[PDB]
Length: 459
Image (cartoon, rainbow, N blue to C red):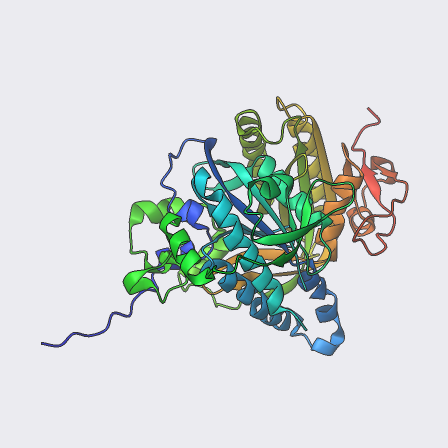
């Protein structure tokens, strides 16, 4: 009696799970919104802006109309390597957002110390990939999770001091650096490492991982796997993710698909070509920032984000805008919204982005606990595609206009701002805008004139 090999692990549910972290895939939580949960862990933030900066290189005519294809190929080659390191070291890639990868090692509190060592080693091996670059911030401590959305769509955020800390840490780093948050440094095993102080900060820089003379990392890591719920093991020790082993389960797939864009699900269902979403396309970015007095307290900010989300989604529906990403910044929550800019009725479409931005601004400004709303609007060619590893990847939009809208919302807080392409293209009367002072914006290559969208009336 024969014993044929299994092969089939390519079900729709498995394909969907590539686009999500274990936090969600194995989360099994209520479908009430907002939903909040609380745990501890170690966070890694890998700035890959040095890679995403290649949108400019691949815009050249030299690439003969295959710039998007070449860009996705070379990005996925390098990012895949980073992903594999994270996954092999036991981490959960949470999101590809803000030209960074955010990863989590969720553990009980007593194990933070040893898991930090695992994460430092991982960080150093990541840098080791690109010798002949990236910046890494590490944090540890209390983490909160927020899931928000409606009956068809779901999003999540992780929130809290450790989340604030991990982006602050990475922001202090130079290329090739690993920076620890103050709490990470307080919680770590100091015998493992040599650090130096970072001027005007309580964060530290890892100079070396130099363990004690009898230390054996492989045996240490094996001990640490006791605390890693989903580390692939036994029969499945050859897999990068346990999620590769998911079987059909209609209830679970119904819940997981809500996190994934419909055009992605179309590809997953083999109803559109696998390369259709890798493209340089003209869009309008509407980047919405919501600031809160207490950005670490899920209990306060979670209802506000849910209420904002319900309104945002309703306004986007009217114009098939999409939410590409939601992620945290230092004082609040950012929504990266995307509109088609096909240019079949240029004044009409850019007018719509602007009107949607103002609607969102007006509504979110009256949501309890939202202290400041800021919206940046930029229009132009952007790279779109599914970026990451076969087993862990996400649809992403990258480019100078994404970065411009992001910076506008931070350097011109409390208002709706637009670039020159958007202003000019709208054909709206000029008195609906205000020409703004020029600001030198970190990371922005000469913005052109910027404008406030003042709106229809003098007021």
